[PDB]
Length: 162
Image 1 (tube, rainbow, N blue to C red):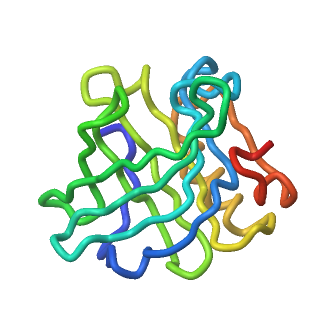
Image 2: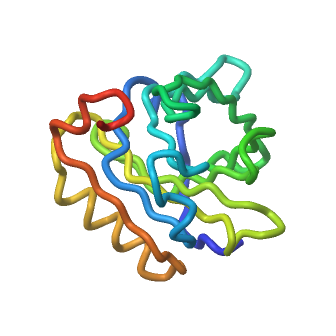
Image 3: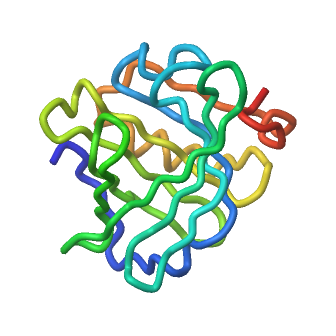
């Protein structure tokens, strides 16, 4: 209830496939600080299950190696909102998407949302897409973000963006 932008009519089947975390922003610098930061995850693939849920495959530098973790987002009454009984927070909201190029989502903690708001701009190809980065910056003008990271093409093809 902080993020005011949501996708009217999301077809979770069409967002299936491979995605690249082109940019990420959070309300707390320490949330995305170092490579070992708790909410510094890189999306690899979204696989919507027939049941309505969504399987998310992501990379994260855990101990001292790029670990691949599999998280699952259960659907809810609203088609753009998903729950995850996973990392700190619990709600996943899909803000906008044209299905073929970009996707902007934001994770939010229910009780401590301002202390846990991370958002990303997912793109389909390892290219710096200006129109997606503009729409991302847009949906973020109204949010309390304090750190914003962006990645280059060569970095996008590396596991964990090294």
